[PDB]
Image (tube, rainbow over all chains, first blue to last red; front, side):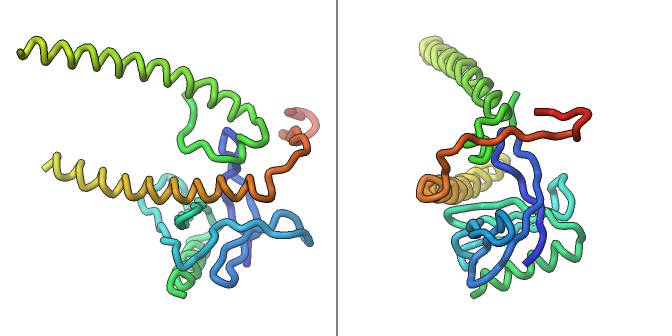
Length: 93
Length: 51
Length: 54
């Protein structure tokens, strides 16, 4: 569970920081403290994980699943590899 | 012109980024059809010229 | 060589678009299911009180 940056659903697609949880082969995001969560990808066993070497954006990954995709961006090269490996173990569940 | 892959956040809050993207995708659709339909009469004309 | 390399790429693109649009149809589905909301959306202030953009 931890902080990540993502892109908004506004017409400019502006970047924004939210707190994300990986649990029970699912990825959810928290929308306020002490309030119900929203699902980001329905399942992780049906995801692939993009390490994005040709992107302009720095420390970013992309998680692409059958019903839903999400671009995300972390604060360090450590955190990229640790969020990419957590999804990658999750994809093997 | 507008940004690619227009996602649902902007759509449902009636943003000006949405408001301008919808302005510009319709104007792109009028240019596109006209150029396709020109490319269509010109590819018609090409076969007629070949034949 | 270009006819092949454009072609191999277009068939990965179509399978990639199929999947991206599958993923987009299911998320499209989801918003309408239970979380779309009926209240007016809120004007978003930025650039503090001295630019105060709203």
